[PDB]
Length: 52
Length: 52
Image (cartoon, rainbow over all chains, first blue to last red; front, side, top):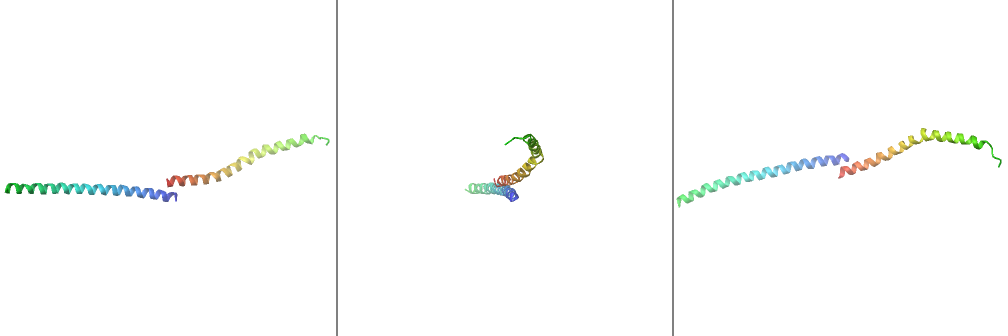
C-alpha cells in the first residue's frame, strides 16, 4: 500500500489541477457575459435618453 | 593440583579457535541478522514516508 499512497497522491493532485482549472474557466466566462450584458444595457439606455 | 604444561598447550587451541570464529563465523552472522532487521525497519519507514 506504499503505492496506494502514491496512487492517491497522483489522483488528488490531478483533480486539483482540474477543478481549479474549470473554476477559473467558468469565472472567466461569467466575466465575459457580464461585460456583454453591460453593452446590451448601455446601448439600450441610450435609446431611452434620445426618445426623452 | 600439580600444574602441567597443558596450561601452555591449551592456550594455543583457544587462541586458534578465537582467530577462526572471529573472521569465518561472526561477521557472516552479523550481516545475516542485520540484513533481516534493516529490511523491516526500512519497510515501515518507507510506509510512513508514503502516508505523510
